[PDB]
Image (cartoon, grey):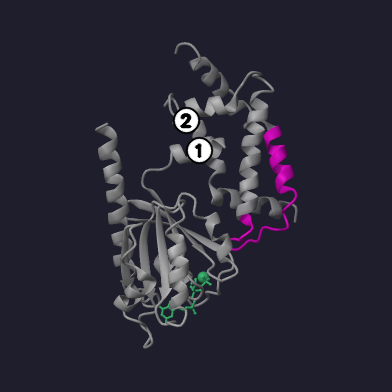
Amino acid sequence: SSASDAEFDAVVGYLEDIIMDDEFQLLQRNFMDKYYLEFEDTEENKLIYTPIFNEYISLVEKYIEEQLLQRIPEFNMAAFTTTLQHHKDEVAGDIFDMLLTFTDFLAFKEMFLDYRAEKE
Amino acid sequence: GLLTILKKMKQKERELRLLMLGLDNAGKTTILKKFNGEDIDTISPTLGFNIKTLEHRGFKLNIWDVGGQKSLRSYWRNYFESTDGLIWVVDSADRQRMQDCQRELQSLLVEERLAGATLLIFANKQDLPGALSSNAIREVLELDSIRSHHWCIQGCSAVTGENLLPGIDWLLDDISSRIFTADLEHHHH
Ligand SMILES: Nc1nc2c(ncn2[C@@H]2O[C@H](COP(=O)(O)OP(=O)(O)OP(=O)(O)O)[C@@H](O)[C@H]2O)c(=O)[nH]1
Ligand SMILES: [Mg+2]
């Protein structure tokens, strides 16, 4: 520690909580639930996967911050990021390794293919 | 936001992002395929993009091949982000559109989202009788006299898989040596 090394660690607490919740599965289910159709099971990717992929990311993180303050009011994502984004290399944990799974495109394509397969 | 920055801060050290671009028909998808030892006898012109994750010389290389059709080139820059190396593939036989190859390349070198990538130019379809000599492709495209990026020309045949390795082998030497000076200047400051 000492002083707002807590703040960060207390935010980490939820970077498990929030994303391990079955409510996180919903917004995904729901977002995927409007393009089952437009995800072909071929190795060549559609030019339109990328714009959907970017909407997906800006929804995951848009949800994460509007959930971090549903619990920690007076929480600032831009302040959290900046500092975290260097001055606490208490990063690196089996924690954000989870959180950047959403940046992996092929892991996104694969899980998206599993969804169209499921409702067919 | 967060996830986009997070990934760019704890990015894998020996993971390289390779973007393959160039006019249609050039042989981009042919190269990718004839690299993993896949069948080239099935390749239809790409309207989207192929990603072929592949290991070589201790690196794992995430190679993106994007469709080169004229109506798809606007959307090319959705893949500029985080590019470690830019593979420009040239159909050295279609000399009529070599004029076009110069314009599209000179517009890529000044993109600032690609500002760091190392430039590998593939003078493909060298097996063809109509194929221009690498040096004639060098004065064309105005390859030299570009104070933007580190570059190398490589005349190759993607069907036989000739000279595809000498190019990628060079690319890493450049990229890794660029990452050498990263650590060197990092720790000493
Ligand atoms: N003779 C000869 N033909 C080649 C060679 N490489 C590729 N081709 C041919 O060029 C044609 C186009 O191959 P592609 O891999 O689809 O070229 P491309 O640049 O990816 O085309 P786009 O998907 O539109 O970007 C195919 O018919 C290949 O057989 C080569 O080295 N020699
Ligand atoms: Mg192609």
Mark 1, Cα crowd under 10 Å, few <14 / some 14-19 / many 20+, is some
Question: With B98 as the anchor, is B182 left or right in this view?
Answer: left
Residue at image position (55%, 55%) is B78
Q: Is residue B97 above or below residue B3?
A: below
Circles 2, 1 touching at the beta carbon (< 8 Å): yes
| x and y, in percent, of residue A40 in the image | 65, 61
| x and y, in percent, of residue B64 in the image | 48, 59
| x and y, in percent, of residue A118 in the image | 71, 51
Q: Is residue B131 above or below residue B62?
A: below
**CB of mark 2 near ligand 1 (< 8 Å):** no
| Front-most of residues B145 and A30 | B145
| x and y, in percent, of residue B72 in the image | 58, 66
- Quadrant of the image occupied by residue A113: bottom right
Residue B133 circle label = none
Mark 2, Cα crowd under 10 Å, few <14 / some 14-19 / many 20+, is some
Residue at image position (32%, 78%) is B136
The quadrant in which the C terminus of chain A is found is bottom right
Residue B37 at least partly seen: no
Residue underneath mark 2: A85
- Quadrant of the image occupied by residue B157: bottom left
Residue B5 circle label = 1
Secondary element at tag 1: helix
Residue type, mark 1 in image? Ile
The CA span between labels 2 and 1 is 8 Å
Residue at image position (48%, 69%) is B29
Secondary element at tag 2: loop
- Identify the subunit bearing mark 2: A
Question: With A86 as the anchor, is B150 left or right in this view?
Answer: left
- Identify the subunit bearing mark 1: B
Instruction: Decide whether residue A25 is among the magenta residues.
Output: yes
